[PDB]
Amino acid sequence: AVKIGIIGGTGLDDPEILEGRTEKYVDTPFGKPSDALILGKIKNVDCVLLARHGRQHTIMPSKVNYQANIWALKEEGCTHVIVTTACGSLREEIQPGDIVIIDQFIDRTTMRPQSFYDGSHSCARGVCHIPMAEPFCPKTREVLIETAKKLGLRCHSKGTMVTIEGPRFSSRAESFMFRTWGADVINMTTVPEVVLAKEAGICYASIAMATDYDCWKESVDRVLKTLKENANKAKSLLLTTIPQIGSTEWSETLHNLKNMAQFSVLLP
Amino acid sequence: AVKIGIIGGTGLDDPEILEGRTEKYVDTPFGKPSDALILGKIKNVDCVLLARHGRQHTIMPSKVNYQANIWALKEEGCTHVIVTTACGSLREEIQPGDIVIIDQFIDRTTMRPQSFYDGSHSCARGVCHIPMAEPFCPKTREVLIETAKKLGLRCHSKGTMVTIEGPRFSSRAESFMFRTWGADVINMTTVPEVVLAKEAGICYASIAMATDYDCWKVLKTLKENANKAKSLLLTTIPQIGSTEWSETLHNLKNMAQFSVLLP
Amino acid sequence: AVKIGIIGGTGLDDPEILEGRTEKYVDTPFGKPSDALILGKIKNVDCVLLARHGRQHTIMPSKVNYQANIWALKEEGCTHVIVTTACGSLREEIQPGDIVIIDQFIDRTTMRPQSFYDGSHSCARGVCHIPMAEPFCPKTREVLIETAKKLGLRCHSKGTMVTIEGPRFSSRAESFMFRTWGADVINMTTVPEVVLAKEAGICYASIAMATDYDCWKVLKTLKENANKAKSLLLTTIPQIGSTEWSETLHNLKNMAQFSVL
């Protein structure tokens, strides 16, 4: 019995994707989420859609309440969270329009809370050191990859996302430097989203859409065109991927995530 | 009608550079600037001088009000902001006493707001993703570069500045690490000043003065550097005032306005 | 005359270490330290033990009040602070159970104040730029190195620590990239602890105990490390007591004072 959190970023602020949709506002112990939860369905599978930046795209990446967002999805009984993110490419072979099913991340954020266990909440007591060797759910990633192959989508099977604080773009020096650190794509929103998802014991996976090369590489209209196409690629990828997920067993996987998440907490 | 904002850093807390000096505190939606603005002129060019750390150098770099400093200068009607910075050298060929007219930076700061568009000020609404592929004004830089040449100053034409949070200096491991990153010089104040200037649509350039090599390899050199930097400024500013800036300024403002996503 | 501050990290939250335990809760202009200072002696050397995370290990690395901790140890008269840290290893040659008398750090923290001189406390006036070229006391590190040999402990003589913000662990890609930066071991507590000890003019060194390989490549080896660290401390501290320091502290004290503008 699965329930799929879906976080929609840039170009997917308010996407018509769910059947039988209901609007639901919640509060959480970490504050309010970016916008109403959108309860709904794809084929037979229960989904919950949420606009990372709010449905009018009014919340900058530094100010996204990632804690509230993941907590609200957890609380609504989500088993998976699949997200999208418009990103810059740091690699010749990752072309504008390409999907990257990222497997790793490099944190360059500085102002964002990264744990539920901050010692200030009684819903999250103790000190948690969550493991990050494998931040993304490999089975959910496997299905995303398989399904994009089916759809005939240009797709990369792994990649390391460097997440910057923003809101500014990179400098050229930084773009070049990120390359030397082994980053493949860049954005402002993966961290700490992915980190909090692990703490919450939720299978998390990210659909990264390369909207353009970052400034290392030697037109707004071209970028907005790429971005709109990318959004439609991502929409089908989700529409086709989510029913595949709803047709396999997950209690196996989910028991191991819930355990890694409990076992990272140190009691007083 | 240019008007040059000038931000004095280490060694330039309280220089006497302007004619017809006048002084006033000013307010901004972002808080108090580091100190009173000093108004005055260099030849026929209107200038605004501001001490980055206060005139008594009382403000540490993580505590500098970058937003108010740049907003103040903008509201005063500045077209340009030319700044000095006392830096360390990460490169053998950038010798103590050299000037670097930097053209890139790497961010190592952790505590500083980098945008006016934080969602909480009526004067800056929207989400702004400002491009930083080319963070300093190349045209302002080019005049600085040419003027340094005419003055016979040891001057490098470009360089990448790594801005650390501070106020502590870098470990030796860190200094070596920054070299592997392609950093050329190191300081505490370039980020976010430079980012906020672009968001403001002001032409920004930075005269960086190597006081020493960083620890991978003070006071007297620092005094000589301020005097070279002051000379560069006195000679550059009348050149900026004698050339045309409308298209440059129009390109900056358009890029900035284009960066802003409204509801 | 010397007095040895001792900060105990993970596995050393409340060690049975000092002769004649006297419990002293203090306050500082930066807040309360993680817990009571424990006063005591080891072979006639005046010591002050402190639990980094509190005696029940309740405070996470990001929330440790490093300013209150260093300041309290300093007011107490400490000439030296020797600390323990439970770390990950980023090198094949640094195995679980090995000790590393670290000599460098790479800062990867984001949330943490790294100075006393913040312009808001009158006990610490002005702008201070503390040199960090040699963050750890070479004198104190040597004594620790010799003793560890004398004790039969696997021990590396130098090493660069990367201090990440946490509380999460590193991703693989971060862990590979730290190696290429030149880090050898990875923790969450060294920075700004080391930095504040320098400002304070106190001799600082750190016993880093590798509990595992970080993910580029358990609870048992931690308990064993704890023991090895206790030993190293019990034996190291009297050697320091029976050596001369006047010149070292003078130079530390002077560098600290000349860093303030």
Image: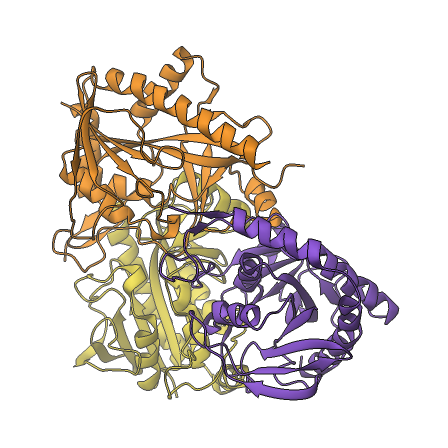
Chain colours: A orange, B purple, C yellow
Q: Eyeballing the image, is B190 above or below A215?
A: below
Residue at the image position 25 percent from the left and 48 percent from the top: A67
Residue A208 coordinates in the image, percent (x, y): 42, 31
- Which residue occupies the foreground of this view, C202 or B200? B200
Quarter-wise, where is residue A262 in the image?
top left
Q: Is residue B228 left or right of residue C142?
A: right
Residue B118 higher or lower than B151, as above or below: above
In this orientation, which residue lies closer to the viewer: C186 or A247? A247
Which quadrant would the N terminus of chain C be assigned to in this image? bottom left
Estimate the x, y position of residue C89 in percent, counting from the top left: 41, 47
- If the image is split into quadrants, where does the C terminus of chain C sit? bottom right
Give how far across and how far down residue A175 sits, in percent: 57, 44
The quadrant where residue C32 appears: bottom left
**C167 relative to A234 in the view: left or right:** left
Q: Place residue A248 in its image quadrant.
A: top left
Residue C46 in view: yes
Left or right: B31 in relation to B178 = left
Residue at 38% in and 58% down: C208
Q: Is residue A144 above or below residue C36?
A: above
Inspect this view and state whether residue B156 appears: no
Residue B150 in percent (x, y) is at 87, 68
Q: How many marks?
A: 0
